[PDB]
Every structure is written in C-alpha cells, then in structure tokens.
Amino acid sequence: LVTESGGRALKSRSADYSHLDWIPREKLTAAQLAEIGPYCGGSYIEPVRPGMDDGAPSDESPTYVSAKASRYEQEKQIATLAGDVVLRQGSMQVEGDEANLHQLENRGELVGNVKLRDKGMLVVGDHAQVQLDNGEAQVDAEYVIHKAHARGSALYAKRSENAIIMLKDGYTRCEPSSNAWTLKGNNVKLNPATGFGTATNATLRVKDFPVFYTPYIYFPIDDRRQSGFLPPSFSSTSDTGFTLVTPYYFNLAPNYDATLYPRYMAKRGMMLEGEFRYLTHSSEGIVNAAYLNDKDDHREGFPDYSKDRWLYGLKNTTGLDSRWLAEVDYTRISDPYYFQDLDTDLGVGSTTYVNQRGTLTYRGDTFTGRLNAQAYQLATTTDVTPYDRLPQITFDGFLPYNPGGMQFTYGTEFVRFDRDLDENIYFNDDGSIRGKRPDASLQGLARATGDRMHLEPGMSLPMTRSWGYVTPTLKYLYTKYDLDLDSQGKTDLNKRDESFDSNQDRSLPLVKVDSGLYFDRDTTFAGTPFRQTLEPRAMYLYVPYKDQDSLPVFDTSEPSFSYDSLWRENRFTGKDRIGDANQLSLGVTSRFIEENGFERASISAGQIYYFRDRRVQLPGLTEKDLKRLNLDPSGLDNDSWRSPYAFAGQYRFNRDWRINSDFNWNPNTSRTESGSAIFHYQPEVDPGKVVNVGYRYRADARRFDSSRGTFRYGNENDIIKQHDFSVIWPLVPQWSVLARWQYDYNKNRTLEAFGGFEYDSCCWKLRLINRYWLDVDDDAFLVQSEKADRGIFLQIVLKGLGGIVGNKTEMFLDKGIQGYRQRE
Amino acid sequence: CGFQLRGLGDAQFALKEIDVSARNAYGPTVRELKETLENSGVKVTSNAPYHLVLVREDNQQRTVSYTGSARGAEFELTNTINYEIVGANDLVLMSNQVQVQKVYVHDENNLIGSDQEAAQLRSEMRRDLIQQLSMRLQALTPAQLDEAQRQAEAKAKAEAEALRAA
C-alpha cells in the first residue's frame, strides 16, 4: 500500500492495473492473444503515441508540451505546469500531475502520477527529478517492459552522467496479481555500454519467501545478448542419488551458441560439462567436453578402470556448398564404463561404442571420390575389438553417355583393415580364472588383418516405357586381399588341417535382369479420389559360386530378410562374401495417391525363388560349423526353393498420424521370422497430444557370437519381442500427463517405464517424472548383466529467463517419446 | 480389378523447365534428383522460371529394440527432406516435407559391418525420397504455379508494400 510491499503490483495506484498498461485477456485483439500463452490473464500493450518508432535523438525533434494550467513563483525561481502534464520529444514521453522547473539549478521535478515512457518501456512512480545540464535523474517506483511481458519495482532508481542506472531493492514475469516469484537484487547496476548489469544481495523469492541467496551476480541487459540461465533439473537416481544440474546458456551470436552443464551428484562428485554448437550456410558442428573426478569406487579392480572420467568430441560438417565436403565425427572417452555410469540423462540404450571418423568427399558431376579414416572406441569390456578402416579410398561413378544407349558404371575401393586384439586373461586370488576378454575367443582367419582392393565395372541397358521397364545389367567384381596373420592364428589353422595363403583373389561376374509393369486404377474411397497404382516387379540374378571360406570377414554382414532383400545384388553387405545367386525375386507394390501427389498409403508383397542352393555364408554357417551336432531352428534354409513371404505396408494421414507395418513368414518351416507394427499420432492442431504404439518381433537375426569367435543364427537370448507404448496427453486446462513403457516379452522384463505430470501456468511450469529403466552393465567377470535403475526427475521453470532453448537434461524424454516438440 | 497400363499422358510431366538447388549443393540426393527429373523430360536449367530448393536434409538415428542384455539391437534410420518452391525474385509458392524410415539390425561385435549395412540402407531411402518427390512434381502444372504466384504476389506486394516511409 502507498509503497512497495513485495509480490504484487501496486493496486492503490489503479484498481485494474491500468497504470501499468495492463489489458485483461477478454479485451485483446487476436493478434495480441497470439503473443501471450494460453493461460495468461492479459497483456501489457503500450498506448500508441506519435514518435514511438522514430528513435529518440536529443534535439532532433521539437518538444511537445501540454498542460492545463501554469504558474510561476518569484522567491524560489520555479516555473510550474499544473494539470495533466505531458511532454514528449520524439520517442521519450513524460506524463505527470505537476511539473516544476527549478531554475536556480536546472532541475525539473515531477509530482503526481508520474509516468516515464520510452519505446516498449514504462516507469510509474510518485516523484522524479532531472538535472538538465548533465543527465542525472532520480525516480521514487515500478516498471513494465511490454515486449518481454516483464514487470518490477524499485524504491528508487538513479542515473549518472555516463548513463549507469542504479536501483535500490529491485524483476518478474508474473501478471500483476500472480506474485508467484520475483527476482530481487538489493543493489542493481545497469550499464548500457558494455551491456552488463550487476546485482548485490541477490535473492530469488517465491510468494515473498526467499529461496536463494548470493552476494554478487552478473547478467546482460542490452536487449537480447549472449547469455541466459536454464531451468535447473533436480533428480535422484539409484547410481547418483540426489542430483542437481544447473545449465547456463550463452547465445553467442545468431549463428552459434554454447551451453554449460555443471552437475552435482551425491554419489559421484562435481561433473563439469559443456557443448558448443554452430551453424552457417556452408557448415555446421557441435563440440562436447566433460570431466569429473568420480568419487564412486564400486568399479575397482575392474578391467580398464579409471577414477578420472572424461569425454571430449567434435562432430563437424563443412563445405556443403562446394564439391569438397569434410565431415568429422570423433569422440574419445576415458574408460569403457563411462556411459554405464554417467549417462543418467538418457536411461535405456546407452551406446556400446563411440565413433572416431574423419571423411573427405569430392563430389564431381559424373563421379564421387571419398577418403575416409574411421575407427570405433568401445564403451564396453565385453565386445570384440572392432576393425578400423584406416584409409578406405573410394571412387564411384559413371561415364557420360547418349540418351537411350549403354550405361557404364565403375566403382573401386581400397581399404586397409587393422586392429590390436586385447586378449588379457584375469585371475582371482586363487588358481582359478576370473574373466576372459572376448578377443581371446577369435581363432584362425578371425585374427586376420590386411589390405583389400576391389574393382567393379558394369554395364546396364535400361529399356523403359510408360507402361513398364526391363533393365538388364552385367557387372564384374574383382577383389584382391593382402592378408596378415599372427603366429597364434597360423597355429590355429595348422590344427584345423589348413594352411594360410596370404595373397588371395576372387573374380566373379554378376548378371541381373530387372523388369516391371505399371498399372493405374482410379477409385474413390471415403468420398476421396485416389489413384491406386499397381507396380509388379521381377528380378533375375545370377552370380556363380566361388569358394570364399578362406577369406576373412571385415565389413560384411547378412541382413535379416525383408521386402528390400528382394531387390539386392547381394544378400551380404560389403565385399567380403558374394552370395552365389541363381534366383528370381517377384513382388508387387500398390501405392494410393491423392490429387496433390502425396502418397497416402502403400502396400508391398514379395518373394524370392531360389533355383540353386545358397552355399557361401558367413564363418560359422558353412561347414566349418553345423558340425556342432544338430543344425539350428531355421538356419538350415539352404536348399529350399523359396524365400519367406515378405509383407510391408504404410498408411500416412495428412501429417497427423502414420502407421507402418511389416511381416515376414517362412513357409519352409511354418514359422514367423520377423514382423512389426508401428503407430505414431500427433495432430497438427494440437501437438500436445502424442501417442506411440509399437510391436517388434524378430528371431531371424544373424549376429556375431562374442564367445564362439564366429557367427550364429538362432540366438534365443537376443530374440526381439517387444512393445513400446508412450503417450503425452492433456487432462484438464493446465495439466498434462506423460508416460512411456517398453516391455521385453522374450525374457518377461520391463526395459523402461516412466510417467509424470506437467503443470503449466502463466509465469511458471512444473514437471515431475518417476522413472525406472534397465542400464547396460558390465560386471567384474566380463559378463553382460542387466542392472535396474530407478529415479525421479524434477524441473521447475520460470518462463522468460532465456531458457527457451533445448535442455540436454531431458534426453530420456526426447529419445523415449517421438513427438517431444511441445512448442509453447 | 479395373486397371490399365500407364499411358504416356500420365508418365509425362506438366512442365519442362525447372531449376534445382539444395543446401547440399553437390550431395548425392540432389544429383540423383536432377538425374531422375531429366530422364522424364524436365530440363534442369539455371534460367528456368521455378526453382525447387532442398533447404534441410536430416538423417536421424533412433533405437527401437533391445538385446537380451538391455543393449541396443535394432536402429531406425530416418531420412527427411524439407523442400520449398520459389518463382521470381525469391518468393515462396509451396513448402512441404518428405520423410522415409527403415530399420536394420545392429551387431555389437561387427561395427564395420553395421555401418556398411546402414549405408546401403540410406541409399535405398534416398531413392524412395526421390520417387516421392517426383511423384509430387508430376501432379504439378506450370499453370498452377503461375496463378499461385499471382495470388502470393497479390498478398505480398499489395498488403506489405503499403508501408513505405510515409
């Protein structure tokens, strides 16, 4: 009352906060409503007056004076303007109830409902005075910044000749009545040059009750400049206990910023982390570093343990506008266990490796050359050391040709694979064995390194008409290996009654005919004109059989069967195995297309028919294996004249919901190999509603068995049978619930689960989440295990403090619910 | 039933002159798009009346399945193109996006393998993104663009140019 009693704005001045330019919601334009949130009770809209946008130069504009009466006193030489006094000069305007000019000094005084106005700025006070010789001024007071919807007050405010403003007992975003939270600096200094301000005896108060103190604090004030503070994240997990993370954001420039994440963790220590992001017309990049001296010694005497824990990396891409493209993707970590311990911001799916990659790419018109240095650093102790491609030179392209003639294509690769096997053996205090590194299970050619060359020319004759096409094509593939093998791996071959042939070459032709038709029927379903298409397709593929059981495996894998398996020249990837093929793939697609050409739904089914047997396979699915007594479940799919049935299908509904699904049924064994259905929902009108439902089954994986040194097919331990549900939905005008659950049927365990609410209001916002997940875990015996983690996540948000920028403390919400882009 | 073979009227496009620009000026995506458009009879000219621009292209990766040991087992690659069309003096007519996503099987103990696999998979996705872009250009007419541009200028030059000094 009559003074600044904290919390709310002075209601004694006006009943309805008219003096702050406050207009309630029911009297605002739609254009103005569009600038405030859904729950805000009104806005500060500055009255329109001549000269708001002309700038405010000193004597550039005539002074506009207006008042109802004037008077003059003769003993103290003061000239007074009574009545409703208003004085503008360009941008700045000044309203008062009485305006005294003390002419003995040069002092203008203002008594009455004093309003100081500038562009987007209002000050309302009881008294103000200015020396006219040098700019010195004092105000006795509350202030509105209309643009930022901010308000505040000060017992007084002063301005010195060099323009430095001082406030005693000072800011908030809340609507006048709200009093929800205020930032109060006992002594505030605002420098317009240098653009920095200071508060001493700085206090964060909530409902007039202090909750945070510091005796000094810095902050920018020059419009929007390169700083801000982010909503802190108070969390608690089972491997970090109580956690506080208080990120700080630098808006360094319109093309790059940087963020700084200090975390305190009860069970860990003070982890310091930071990222720098940049973006230009021709480049983009992000740099990450983090350090922590970890106080947790649970992983003592573990292999490759480090009590220091750090990560640095750069992910960079420059020269998108030029034929030269330089990408980097490099990360290094201190110890394997890093993400198993410090990745509590993500929960489920901590990575088991980190990329270390540089790549140069020249991208000509006809051809493309690429030099690529690439390695991997393992975030686990239970995986075999990966090979690294130290050079991989790559030229791919064609020869300029006449329309309707031949098409000559060439591709070459040179690449040098290497690795340093770490096969240490760890024993207990007694005579027995504690743990064996996985590399120790690799034998024979599995321990090989070396260079590989590959030439691949080919010719194609694409005869195509509107009603269909037939494109035959012939390619030749020559590969030459220069291998190296340690003595260990050679003796492993002596025992297998084999010998090591270093120089090894392979030459094979590849004949492939592809042909399909095009059909179009017009239909109208649900009153909509669809142009349903029908495109059948067939591919004949001949590759003669050549024994490749003496060629190591560096970059080759065998993908699971799917609708794309039909159309590929090789059922393996890479160059290390070429699949003896004598086969005809048949399939058909049928797209539904709208008038705009937007594909609204599609369906595809297909099968492959095998005339010959499929003899070349990975190491461990030829005759070097299957010698372990019986054959697996469906691994004995050689000599079967028919691939599985391949079904796929997609339905997208105008960028509001989309559903994808695929099925793969094998009749030779009467068994489903692979299927999945995925549904995603998120309307355009209300991106606050979000629903993800997914099912995934897959048992036909072919992976590398870490203890057998070889590949396997039927791995019952890793059969995927999973459902993933997640939802984000608004219950009642200010409340919304979000949750997610992912369940592993095959072992009947929950992989991740979490749920929480999110209360929204005009000036602040609260998010609370209870969570439980399974973290990737390596134990002391080099055995993978499942380590459940529980946790709780708390976020309190003061709207309007430069924290409208993505927070990295919310990763588990971004990853775990596609649709996290709630934009308000 | 009720089908028929695709006539020459439906395989052909309604325009012939188009300009093609991308943020990845010589990347694989735009090169293959221009190759596809010029094989249907659309001349890709710098002086053409309507520039199609690929302003953002993102290639996110997400995990969808887990192993027996709670590690990642299947990755979903997602390729998304953001495209705009501009006519004269850099004024935008239409704006939309195309998106595709496929999934592969990761191997903890075969990383060079898996990176190869994902690569070949990104290639297949690139061809599908381009099929679905030209599918949208074929349903477009050089007359559609002209009247949409007359309306875009009737909104941009008539309403915005009314505030020029005093």
Image (cartoon, coloured by chain):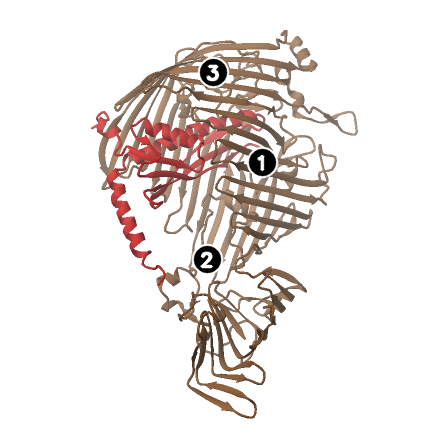
Chain colours: A brown, B red
Depth check: A270 or A504 in front? A504
**Mark identifier at residue A351:** 1
Quarter of the C terminus of chain B within the rendering: bottom left
Whole-percent x and y of residue A199?
A: 63, 65
Residue A713 seen: no
Query: Of callouts 2 and 3, which one flags the residue occurring earlier in the amino acid sequence?
Result: 3
Q: Report if the CB atoms under discs 3 and 1 are less than 8 Å apart.
A: no
Q: Which residue is mark 3?
A: A456
Sequence-wise first label, 1 or 2: 1
The reply to whether the C-beta atoms of the residues labelled 1 and 2 are less than 8 Å apart is no
Residue lying farthest to the right in this orientation: A430
- The answer to whether the residue labelled 2 contacts the one labelled 3, judged by CB atoms less than 8 Å apart, is no
Check disc 1 and give the amino acid type: Thr
Neighbourhood count class around disc 1 (C-alpha, 10 Å): few under 14, some 14–19, many 20 upward: some
For the residue pair A305 and A506, the one nearer the viewer reads as A506
Q: For residue A356, which quarter of the picture?
A: top right
Q: Which quadrant, please, contains the N terminus of chain B?
A: top left
Provide the chain ID for the residue under circle 2.
A
What residue type is disc 3 on?
A: Glu
Give me the residue at 48% from left, 64% from top: A149
Q: Amino acid at mark 2?
A: Trp
Q: Is residue A265 visible?
A: yes
Measured as percent of width and height from the top left, residue A161 is found at 60, 71
- Tally of numbered discs: 3
Where residue A573 appears, x then y in whole percent? 49, 21
Around disc 2, counting alpha carbons within 10 Å, would you say few (fewer than 14), some (14 to 19), or many (20 or more)? some
The picture places residue A69, in percent across and down from the top left corner, at 43, 87
Depth check, front residue: A484 or B14: B14
The residue where tag 2 is placed is A735
